[PDB]
Amino acid sequence: DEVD
Amino acid sequence: DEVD
Amino acid sequence: SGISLDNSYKMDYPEMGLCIIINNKNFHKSTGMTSRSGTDVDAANLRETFRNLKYEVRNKNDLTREEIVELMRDVSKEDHSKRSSFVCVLLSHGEEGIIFGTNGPVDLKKITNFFRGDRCRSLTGKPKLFIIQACRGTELDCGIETHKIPVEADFLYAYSTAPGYYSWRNSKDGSWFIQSLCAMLKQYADKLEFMHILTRVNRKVATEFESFSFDATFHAKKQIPCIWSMLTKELYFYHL
Amino acid sequence: SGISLDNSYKMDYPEMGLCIIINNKNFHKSTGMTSRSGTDVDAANLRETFRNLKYEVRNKNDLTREEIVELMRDVSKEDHSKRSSFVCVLLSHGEEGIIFGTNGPVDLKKITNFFRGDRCRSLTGKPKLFIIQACRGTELDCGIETHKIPVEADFLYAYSTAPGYYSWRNSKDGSWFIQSLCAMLKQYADKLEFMHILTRVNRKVATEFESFSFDATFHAKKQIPCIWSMLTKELYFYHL
Ligand code: NA
Ligand code: NA
Image (cartoon, rainbow over all chains, first blue to last red; front, top):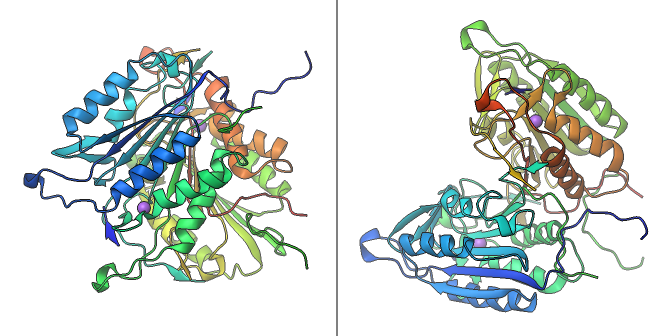
């Protein structure tokens, strides 16, 4: 899970 | 007619 | 029992819920904000419209920024366990993200934060509807000829106008948006899901209204409302 | 003929319309923006999903801010007379009101203005859908346990996340929002009106996803998308  |  | 589906909010609690109407007409002279002629027509239309939907309506007039925040805080601290939903209507001056108390501005985020999923537990999972008649800036539309859940979930913001734009209010008939919203709730609340009602409001405001002004800058202008939905289910005001 | 109603957009033009997908994965080193692992999964899912809805899909990868603006300008200058609608999907970094080209930012307002009712006449009165997977700020959702027409009319912004918030992308599965959107279009495009599809997307993202991180700041976080509708009619991807 990564954020933009 | 008026604006808020 | 038989097969079940869960696509619509439960709206058959003992109470539909509160409808808080904040009607700011007259502003402190030092702010320099003009009086909002026609807003009492809106406030009375909303009271009757939501009365017939069986909301517990509370009308509040000419509240300071301090009174707005205290009212919202106190309402968010009530026990809403027996209530299906919550509705707040704001009628005032505004700019993007802001509505005005009689003596100065309030961040809309400050108001709605009291009702967050984690901060008002008796409304968690229930639809929280904020209906905003207020400017969002000074742009004019010239027209063209033709498990956990997120704390921000289950909010709906029914904005009278697009981000960045003025919102129009007629001093005799009330605001374009509130006029149209009440008319469509009256006609379709026993028939249509709420997003479909608000789409008909969008069409009514967009097609039936155009400003008339002796000032060329403000003449012949149009308006489109803005539905901001973070809802997770369909919303019907009726139940089986 | 018999009685007629006009509550839904005409979607039986010869063509459904264009679906422009801008897939920004790799950014110029000088910007310091990280690569967006998983975005190719999103771009391929969208291409297939909108292919099956009979859109003319055009995928574009790793566009500069200049290339984004030139692409949107050129697309807005095409003749869309035989097309029912227009769809643009933006996959990139972002902040509130902004999406990033590979070398710097573009105002979303700049992109959508090319398609205004008065500036793209062959799309006037037709639905213009912008689907945005990009951050809108750096907030994290902790969750809680459970006639003229306006030039801004007929736009729909299907935002992956609430205003002010990060948006979540899984490096293996794609973004939470695009995953869910494609799944719900696949299942319901021949069944449900578009706002009702996007409401099911809201529920899927809100209930089925939660972040996992070794960093406590970013762990156990939730997301709600944001439907911004200025549409004036119901939108069905099918026709009779
Ligand atoms: Na209005
Ligand atoms: Na996402």
